Length: 313
Length: 313
Image (cartoon, rainbow over all chains, first blue to last red; front, side, top):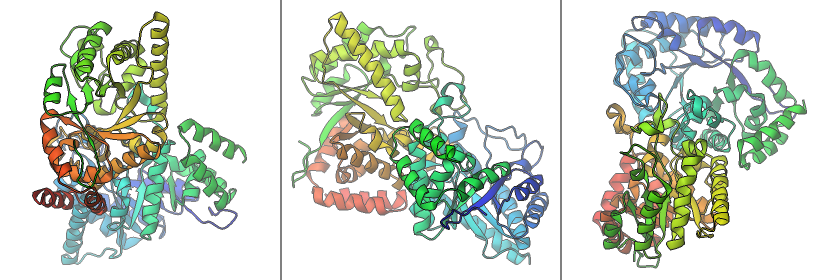
């Protein structure tokens, strides 16, 4: 398992986007699913996914992971996507628009269908709910209110769910990182989504060819937001995960270990590589390295240092 | 002067978008021009503004201000605006795209023409340069390198500029606030652009009516970034300004004052109103109100508190 020579234990989980992916996740040592993307259930179809179709998908993954935690992220879709049954409005900047949790709060019918399926799946294993695109504690409160509604609905129908199901949020909007202490009081965990956190924090559309060079997850700015979220989570006794691609990056492994990240979630094939690094760097050394990294000025300084750290393999 | 009874002074400046705006600024008691928007020189024309046209504009504002500091912001335009001669690319998210300083560093011929006019204008008064849409220190250093190249050009041409000319940045990308301590080593001042800082920090397009209830400049997240910038500037002996619309908002005046903001730049008409608030609130009391505002969790609590604070003045 991923434990430093001096005894610091971390959890390595897998990001998946379909029911099939569980096989590779376990074969590569995944202790759980830190990010189950549910977009496969909504894309390339002409009507919304029914509760039962969603339930069967969630159920199969939850059972095949054999009690390991499965963090299911609710729909993270906006008008930038091709969905004919949705009818999205015209948006000049879709990435800053009506999408994901914002759409769900305005379309409770979609949101409750997915929550009902996830909750019913939690009766068969270890399930966690994760909201995307959270900007403020007020949104989490509204989301959790509809979640309690669905619980009450299933209660009235005689349908079982895990009453202790944990609910967390993707931390991908900068306001969520800067107010992590506030959010920490309302959620059971954070998962740092560095992919979009980098895009919003630097104001850089990764899909834009002309400013690609400005997209730098390994930047002083994002690593300071990472530390912000981890510390706020720990101060409230909650655990901090990361499902962005940084968690699978060997150059970031030692920094994240040093910052006290509880859970690395990544593409399954990256798990053995990160595990090896964790097992070959003391937690006390990693803390020093993360401390140096967070006092650096430019992403290049950090890259060179970590390259030298990985070089010492 | 805008000074609290117990002796805390702040500088009240004016935002302007044309040359003629300077008269109103002086008439309202502006101690400077905290933001000279230069978009008027680029918009609604068929060709780039020449150095001499820009120079004559900058020079007149600088002279009429009579030695008061004039902060001139370089071009802040992207493909969201219609400018045929710029040949902007089609972009999915223009606000996250190739604009302002990112364009200037890719098109230094445009950048140097404007910097040349600004530098020449500084021979006639108190001029300061401000870069928009800075996301990293790497960008500031790339922009300053071009500035020094322009200084060397003027030198060998025998043209005069203020060799002590101060250079600062707009703080509107979240990463710039999170790395203020790093940026403070490379700039002479910050100016907080709360308008765009709010949209980026919350990942909300203010122009999106469907989610415009999420646009909240007076949220904990934004005010915490403001404090971040102010503290970082002061640790390096620099001053922190705000030209975003928050600086002209009477509700924010006491918080901004309490956080230690050095300079309030606003539409000239708003200067007397903010001045009256500053002079009728004790700095010691303002610090406590700011501390409370930053410990709060919703934009509702803060605005509700501030409304009472400035009714009781």
